[PDB]
Amino acid sequence: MTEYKLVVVGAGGVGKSALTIQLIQNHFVDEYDPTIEDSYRKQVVIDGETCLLDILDTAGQEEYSAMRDQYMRTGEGFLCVFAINNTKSFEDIHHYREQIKRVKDSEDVPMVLVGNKCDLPSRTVDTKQAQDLARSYGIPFIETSAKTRQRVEDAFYTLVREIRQYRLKKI
Ligand SMILES: Nc1nc2c(ncn2[C@@H]2O[C@H](COP(=O)(O)OP(=O)(O)O)[C@@H](O)[C@H]2O)c(=O)[nH]1
Ligand SMILES: [Mg+2]
């Protein structure tokens, strides 16, 4: 059984919790329910490999979190989430990426860019704008909807695949 420690980062309100809960529980949390920062473990088969995913869904970024500091230090791959109807959250992506590189003191960290809420007609971030940002970082870009269950597994499984390739190349 292969472990992958994943960290979901990005601005408040973009759907990090909704994406993680959809993946873990196949449920969509009610729109107005309290979010909480928490970690989740789930055994899953990914490309025929039996995997243990250890996922931290981050929150409360303006106060100390011992768990978040541990997962940022030790996390193996990062899902950088913005919402496609929220330009500020997309324009925040470079700060989240910079935080990750600083903690890892590395320019080469497994990451996937995720544009969530692709079920909303009020899009303000064009798919091609985000694809270009991801291309400039050298990482995959995936558009998701936690609500209509579009590409949720693809987003997380793609990050696992990025970690697997990182490991294979370094050896
Ligand atoms: N329409 C839609 N709303 C979403 C989606 N994902 C999250 N939300 C809503 O967006 C708000 C923020 O979601 P949340 O998971 O709490 O975001 P976090 O703060 O990034 O964890 C909540 O009201 C969610 O119900 C999605 O894919 N589509
Ligand atoms: Mg949350």
Image (cartoon, rainbow, N blue to C red):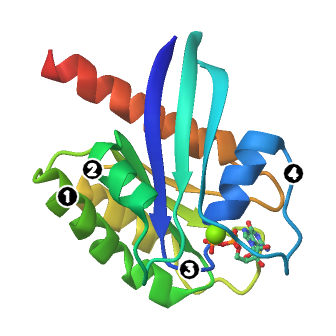
Relative to 34, does residue 159 appear above or below in the rendering? Answer: above
Badge 2 or badge 3: first in the primary sequence? 3
Residue under label 3? 12
Q: Position of residue 102 (x, y in %)?
A: 15, 62
Q: Quadrant of residue 38?
A: bottom right
Image position of 86 (left or right of 165): right
Q: Which mark is residue 103?
A: 1
Disc 1 residue type?
Answer: Val
* Residue 112 visible somewhere in the drawing: yes
Task: Give the amino acid at mark 3.
Answer: Gly
Q: Return the disc, 1 or 3, that comes first in the chain's sequence.
A: 3
Give whichever of discs 3 and 4 has the lower sequence position: 3
Inter-mark Cα distance, 3 to 4? 20 Å
The residue identified by callout 4 is 27
Label 2 crowding class (10 Å Cα cut-off): few <14, some 14-19, many 20+? some
Q: Who's the residue at 24% across and 45% down the image? A: 109
Q: Which residue is mark 2?
A: 73
Amino acid bearing label 4: His
For the residues marked 2 and 3, what is the alpha-carbon distance in whole angstroms? Answer: 21 Å
Q: Residue at x 48, y 82 (%)?
A: 89
Whether pointer 2 and pointer 1 mark residues with C-beta atoms closer than 8 Å, the reply is: yes
The answer for how far apart the CA atoms under marks 1 and 3 are is 20 Å
Q: Residues within 10 Å of mark 1 (few under 14, many from 20)?
A: few
Secondary element at tag 2: helix
Task: Identify the mark nearer the N-term, 2 or 1.
Answer: 2
Marks 2 and 4, Cα distance to the nearest angstrom?
Answer: 30 Å
> SS of the residue at dot 1?
helix
- Residue beneath the point at 52% across and 51% down: 56
Q: Is residue 99 above or below residue 61?
A: above
User: Mark 1 or mark 4: which comes first in sequence?
Assistant: 4
